[PDB]
Image 1: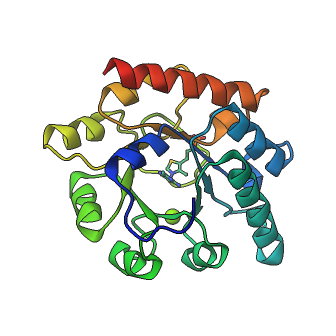
Image 2: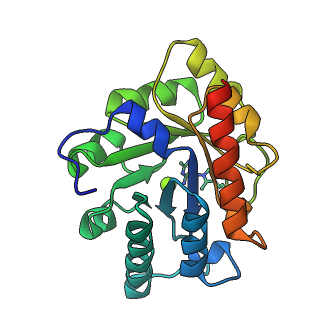
Length: 226
Ligand SMILES: Cc1ncc(C[n+]2csc(CCOP(=O)(O)O)c2C)c(N)n1
Ligand SMILES: [Mg+2]
């Protein structure tokens, strides 16, 4: 449960991606930390701290919120991943960092974080292959379904890229993202993904704990069945 002195195994990474909850203070009307605690109690297997955009906390307020979210993750025994902010990830001794195509180059990031978990968002086959070559531990593929949680998102692709990646014999850990709900997660796993990631399906649920628990149960069933 400490800092990694060796890169994560693919088997372990795939287990962590099962129910990957992502959240920032501006993704819910409830108390931010409380929602994160409920998501973890319910069954989320991985959590990503993503605090950006308008209304998002900044400065010291953002750092203190990150510390509380990381504490919640430690209590639940779930890894804490930071989005974009490499310096914050190192400063908090986070378990990982997630970056996109317009963020810091993956090769640069991999060198700066040692053996920490590294996730990269990809939308094309070329980007997936480049991410693997750069040292990524997993790729986030989407948007699978329509979503407006994230402002400028690329064209909806369903599970097409997930399928294409597996058909080429690429076994890198994959997590699907974008408009995923309790009702539409099955196809994502069936296509070859190792889990599903979401924001609103849990953060804006009238019952975050039950939603996370439903996800955890469903994904387990889907993985055993494919
Ligand atoms: C693992 C990973 N893959 C992709 C992204 C970028 N991203 C693409 S769609 C989306 C919103 C989903 O919200 P909703 O579930 O409410 O549609 C985000 C944050 C990321 N941060 N982490
Ligand atoms: Mg980014």
